[PDB]
Length: 100
Image (cartoon, rainbow, N blue to C red; front, side, top):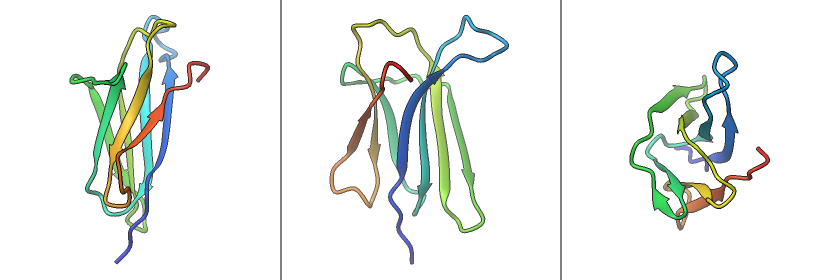
């Protein structure tokens, strides 16, 4: 058996074809096993609607999750990603850094 804790990156992107759109992204990468819970949070509250979740695996069976959705950030709001995984003794919460 193998277990590997996910790497977690939280960042924002505009599609180049439409700069009127801002997306918040959680890239959860390289994890074993694939069982996982991933949420985006705004000011500590779960964002229910997340339009996109792209899931893949590598040759060695590691999982790669891109979880992302359109959002309209203000300087006031705190965004974060909350991950629950067998490798984590408590849920891991990773904040969005505004300048990313």
